[PDB]
Length: 196
Length: 196
Image 1 (spheres, rainbow over the protein chains, first blue to last red):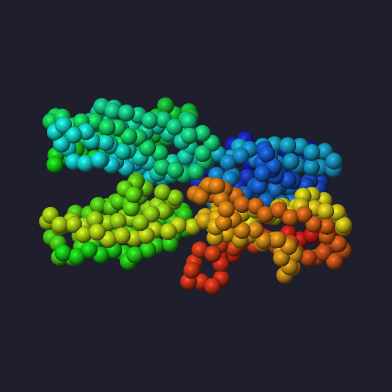
Image 2 (spheres, rainbow over the protein chains, first blue to last red):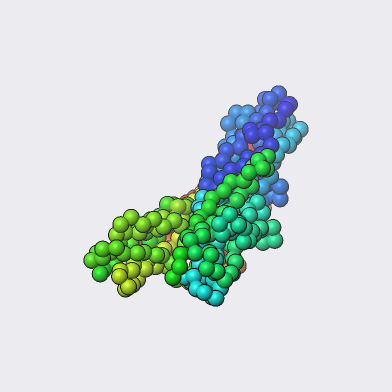
């Protein structure tokens, strides 16, 4: 008999989506299907078997669904396996700029540039520019197996010179969701440096 | 001048929902608003000012929104403040029952009952029942990752007997979030011990 799945090998979903994986056989009269994650942990989905198809529905998809899901199809005593790696992305909010105080001659100010609920972090790079100039960019490959929706941030301290007045701080959050695109997904925020 | 908010002082929201807080003034010609959290951390939401009202839109509401949000209204050189406590919870999925294997009369078998994406844990009770019979109940007032969203489990092993065929295994997940309700919020899964 033969085993097949939809999608063929991977599902990249947005957190909160209704993700449905299916497992089917051909050449088998009475197949039995079972699903599992690579480490036999909870499926965090509901399995429904109908005829020659088994469906694993994870709705809403979340971090507990981020696994290689392996469907094992059994026909008589022969079993076949096929897996689909379920992946999730989250980029729902523009970043936010926060200044320590108003511009003051000789007083360094600290800009906090942050983005909420963005996933995954290892494909997020935050840029903080003043004008078309990059003050600092930040990447996140070290906060390791954290899956949660923590807020990621960039911080830069600088002393305002007379010439900065009326310049625009630009904070850009770039998520490289598509590895086949040179240009990432970007949400940005802008704050005018006005004197006070 | 005067300040006002909607809601008045608190909001219990479900993670994933789109929540809006508005702050207005009366008695002020050209007021200016700003929001901040009790610890001056990111808003993790979007502020929009239209005339005499400011709106802080949190969509989706998530962990970075678990705070008292404070609106600061400014008129002429004077400021007023007024806060709204935003509480959050998550109970988006039915629990998932999982038997250790082949159901055979008299053979000990482990029932793993799990619940995914729950917050907060200390408000959760998972009960494994056999008819109106509680076999085991689990509480989690002890967790090492507060804002986790990690799957919670209850395991029990037992040997059925001939009377148990037909009886349903029932795993109930109760979340007591609502204090003005005498009955916790409930989700359950059932698995019949069917035999040959």
